[PDB]
Amino acid sequence: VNSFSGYLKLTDNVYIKNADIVEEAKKVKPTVVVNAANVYLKHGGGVAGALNKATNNAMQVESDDYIATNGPLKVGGSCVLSGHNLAKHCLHVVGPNVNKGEDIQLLKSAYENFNQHEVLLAPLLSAGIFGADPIHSLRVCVDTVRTNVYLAVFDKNLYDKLVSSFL
Ligand SMILES: CC1(C)CCC(=O)N1Nc1ncnc2[nH]c3cc(F)ccc3c12
Image (tube, rainbow, N blue to C red):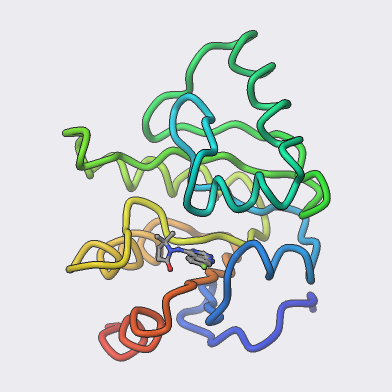
């Protein structure tokens, strides 16, 4: 038993709540929050920029030191850093960016990083809010992650509808 609430059981190990992942994290303070990051860990906007703003830029400061030491992540890769005031840890995961011509098959590799953690609060990766992409991000998540994943989806229409289209 954990402290997640209003999470609609999607499968044996996948759950979802109509929520902003940043606000979910502040309330729950989970062991692991997933950031939908880029390879440079430049948290300018989206979940990344909003989580970082919620850390008062401490996430960015820590990330810049990580990159200066280790260089960029791989598309499909991840690193574990501090969760600051939002979680014990933040798992920064990079899904393919199709607008950069990056192969979306790498989305499965991205979700495989979740299997190294027993429980995670996560947003949708390589999805966005338009077309069959966000819908696609969920199918790969369900078919790839075996650990317990709590998906926060901020957009209601997508939340409402991913549920209604879920096989
Ligand atoms: C793009 C994608 C990652 C996948 C589908 C989805 O809804 N996304 N965004 C978000 N994901 C998680 N929490 C969120 N909080 C928010 C608060 C806002 F004002 C605006 C957007 C979000 C948001």
